[PDB]
Image (cartoon, rainbow, N blue to C red; front, side, top):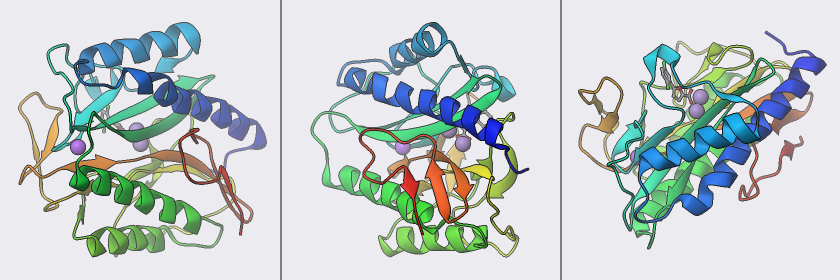
Length: 259
Ligand SMILES: O=C(O)c1ccc(-c2cc(Cl)ccc2Cl)o1
Ligand SMILES: [Mn+2]
Ligand SMILES: [Mn+2]
Ligand code: NA
C-alpha cells in the first residue's frame, strides 16, 4: 500500500518515538546491567513518556517489550534479569512502538565496555550495509537490487547475510508486504513506488550464515556461534529517494536522502 500524507506524518511520529527509545537507553547500556532491566526501562519510557506501546510485547507470543540480542545471538533475544552485559559485548536492542495506529521499527548495535576489533568491524560494516541500501532507495528501483547490494558488500568483508529474516513493509501493521530480503533472490520482484514504507534490517554474521533457534522458542544464535549484528531503520520512499523515519543523533547518514 502507498501511505497517504496523513499516514506518513503518523509514521514520522511513530518512527521518531522508536528512534528516541534507542537514544534514551544508550546511557544504560554498560557493563553490569541486565537485559531485563534495559527492557523495563524501555517499556516504562514508551508507555509513560511517549504514551505509546511496544508492538513486540505479545506479538506472535513474544514475552518482552524490546528484543535484546548479544554477540552470537542473531535476533529475538529475550530480555532477562539474569543476563548481564559484559566488557566487549556487542548488543542489539530492537524497538517497535505503535503510536496513533502506526509502527516505528528500528534497532542499533551498542558496543559494551572496551570494543574488540571484530566487534567494531562487524557492527560498522553491518550499519554500512544498511546505509548503502538506504542510499539506493528511490522510485523505479527493484528491491532485488538492494538486497543484492547488501549481500555483495557484506560477503566482501568475509561476513554472511542471515537468510531466515528480512525487512518488511510497515504501517498500521507491524509486518506488511513487501518482504525486503537482504540478499539476492530470484523470488524478489518489487519495484519501489513513492509512499511505500518499509524497513531494511540486515542481520550479518561474522561467520557462516546458518542459524540455530534455542529452546525457549525465541532466541536465535549463529549455528557456528560467531558474532552477529543488525541495524534497522524504517523509511518512506520519496519522489527522488527516501526519508529515514527512525534516524538517531548518532546516525552518520542524512535523514533525507536526495537523488
Ligand atoms: O524488526 C522486526 O521486524 C522484528 C523484531 C522482532 C520481531 C518479531 C517477529 C516475529 Cl515473526 C514474531 C515476534 C517478534 Cl518479536 O520482528
Ligand atoms: Mn525491529
Ligand atoms: Mn523490522
Ligand atoms: Na548478535
